[PDB]
Length: 121
Length: 121
Image (tube, rainbow over all chains, first blue to last red; front, side, top):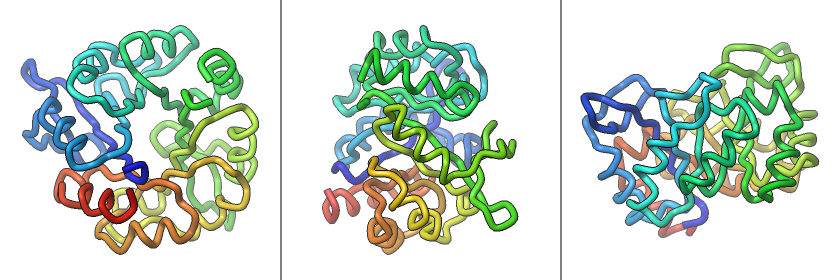
């Protein structure tokens, strides 16, 4: 299972977390709560959980979505989308994320990588 | 280090692999070869390597980019972008990817998750 990462992009639609495909543009009609479980059962090794609701912003990770997903699966959850500053990483971990993903934020401030790794491993 | 995933989006510009930010839209001017090394030194636990050149296609992962990155770092590399069918996963692994990421391909054919996990773990 260690070989498979499932990336899940989700956002709020009418009070429900829905899975989106095609770079966050197509509403699949599949509930996030159902998909997370199925991905675990099928043998995914970790989940890359991207909130389309926070992706591209610097407001922090979507901690409500992390909280929602945490009790539904035992897999490692990688929080993605929204990171801007050091306090955001602790916040994700406190909601049950196992890992944090950074991209633009890392390029623009490489020291974030160092700071997370020295604090959290 | 296990806590940090660095996502790197890259593509070819004038014969060089360049790092892009802002969902693959801004050319940073930073070479992929330099950035991979720096991310390793700074303590990233794994790299999510997305080829903007194959993302959103179903042609396979960008195996040339995986080959290019493999000898530059010892970190686990997650191949991302381009997956369409089972033979693509073996191909990525054979170029040195440690993991494969799937998203739209998994939603559209959940059995891919099962098949990768039973074959590769």
